[PDB]
Length: 607
Ligand SMILES: [Yb+3]
Ligand SMILES: [Zn+2]
Image 1 (cartoon, rainbow, N blue to C red):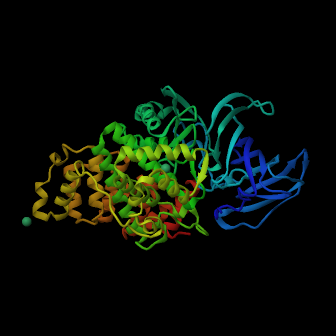
Image 2: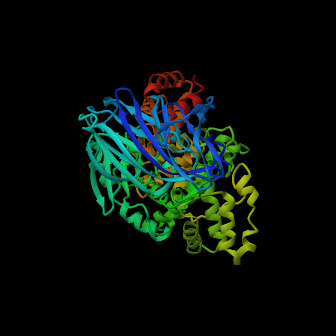
Image 3: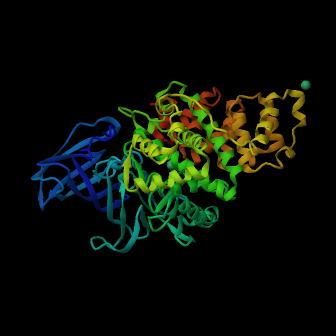
């Protein structure tokens, strides 16, 4: 059972389809419309059901052409408010009906960010975007807001006519709105069943450029050219992903580059991956995020976690496929480099939460926990470590890739648990059960902290990073002169990042070391977001006042949580920048993404 949902579960009734008709009102910051849910009863004599909602105003509920009775229960914090609907005729098992709900969202909808013209690139038009994962779809429309239920959908979205709407669906035409000629109606169809967390909507002054046979890039005009180059590897990754996963079933693979306040690196919305503009490094170096989102087209979007306790299924397997894609393009030594980096990120997470913290378990019990608060690298990298350990145990990547493709085929279009996964693993590898039984399943799956065993990693690309980091850590004042720009000459951007990650793990360093590093390496000049993030964290933790404005600016000019939360936390932990960090958060809070605002508040202990 799904302890993040207040809706009727899948064992009671299942939504099969949603037809959404809505209008986007920028003057009121509301979406208004009707959500027609085709619901199939899973039981005899079904006479009511319950849907999830959050800050929704319900006008009416119509079945068979007449209004029916419904009731909103009391709000249950971040879960929202259950909506019980009294059906007018009892349903038999497998009977389907259509329930048409008239609704309006709140301007404070946790699923949405409304941007003024000034917050966009073009400065003339406002912009709206959604982000439903994990449990924010209930803040857009009433639904069984659980990934245990998969549905198809169609939508008609009325927007001002100078703007474009896109969704996680195939575009199915556009027309002037009959009810308001200042407006255009965009239509959409998603014919593959999806969990409702994959429903998404953007409305803005968007333009497109074709970058492959099945891929357009979408952004504001000012970002199209740069985005098209940055993401030019996308077709080549889709082809590799198909090789590993089986056919791509979703038709189009388009990219949307969001405004800077997008809270994640990417979001795998089907047919339309959303990405942060912090990927726009100029050299394609952050394209592992594209590979990740592509991979979700199998792991997550086809095979889906049944509840958010089992989020590692989605993420661990996607990181495992991500790193194969990058390995195929750039070499097996690069795959091992990325893998070992990921372990370092897992070390960081575990150290941050503490080694006995429940959020460091692979499978987590989210009863009474907000999934947004529990969100971290753990499901990604502990999950990835488990799978790379199994790869090693079971005979190598070719063999384990056979299991991954079989797994995807087995559970396509379904929602599953960890036990489902484990059962199939044992079934696939039945000739190697004795090996599988050496795994400490309880510790890997259910214990906090670092995993009980670390995989083997090729070190070839990592060695230079470690060596340089170690030179800086062990340097005394009289050693600082020996550093020079030539130290970096054979390092890729990836290796520079890893050098910084390695060094950050032993921060602070002496202030004079950090000043020297700027003198000889000019890291202040680097706009690669991953590198600049780590460098600024290293500067702030080492108490360099000159970095304060740089860190404040990066924290606020974009909103990717990966970067914004630790930058604010570092700035708050430094006595010299503490009051400014808090003041800056207070000044920016009303114009931040709502989830990011909430989490940065909790981190700073402000409100
Ligand atoms: Yb010395
Ligand atoms: Zn992911």
